[PDB]
Length: 7
Length: 368
Ligand SMILES: CCCCCCCCOCCOCCOCCOCCO
Ligand SMILES: [Mg+2]
Image (cartoon, rainbow over all chains, first blue to last red; front, side, top):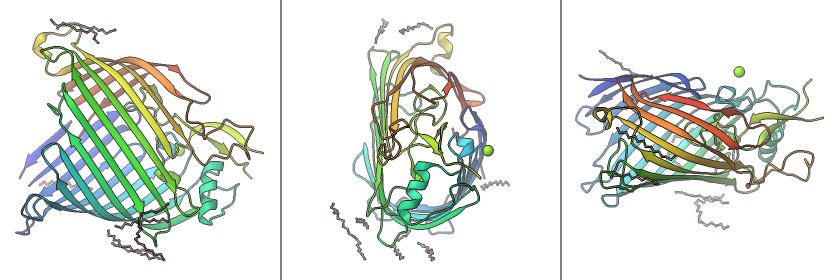
């Protein structure tokens, strides 16, 4: 699992 | 910019974690900045990335790296030692065309070895360097500073990144020590993957993988053992415990020698795999694009070109490249909600003295 969150 | 956190698992790696952060454009410089770290049962790695894809107008990229790495060899199923290292890399990237890219770079690395369990092959390298620690003690230390020229070539004509069905991928990476370094050596790695679709819908694909490694010393020195190649495990020869293929430690007596089943890798390696990709039995067509079954034949060897079978005639000739391990089995890949997943079951039909078996192997990824 990999979670990616653009800021 | 962005950040990310990963959690994964592998049979050889254990529960693994990852996280990173990237500033898409560092205050007008056009150099992207990044911080990444990962950690599994035997390796802790961190880096600062500083790259610009357009160092020149026509595509050439300029890359910087600053890294720290902690490696526990016992937890990577090798004879025991500890290697803590740090350094920097400056890499230029040249895209030759659509399917080819080249890279050249200069690198600095400091390696600090400790906790080395005395064995013949390891000590043999230490002797080549002028280092002669006790053969009966595991409280030692060896430190080196190295400067390297790094080259690389990547061919990629894969029809698709997830579940390729057609085309090839080739990756050649080399390095050589620049005079003035404590170590004197070169090292080459070659990886190839070729997908041949045998049907029009591309559901029946034949896959050939090869992996080759070779490196030796220059000037009477050897290659550092912490630069060794390995084989066995989920990504090389399935059905074999990770890194088990190749020479085994010949241990010095503690306070004459002792044969072991602790693999130490080696400075030459060769792995090949033939895999038949098929549609997946007992799964709906709705879930086809997300699963891949395959049946494979894997093989590989690892050897120590400087093993002196004269001085040690009572042991197996570890310089022998022809003890080729083999396995066959079935694999399953699934793009799961928990991320890329891989089951494999393999029987190592051809194995040798001290080779450990790992029939069921399992991996959930954390990068994708
Ligand atoms: C005190 C020695 C300083 C020497 C510095 C040399 C730095 C760059 O070296 C260039 C080496 O050239 C590589 C050419 O490759 C030919 C290899 O020849 C070996 C034949 O077996
Ligand atoms: Mg331990």
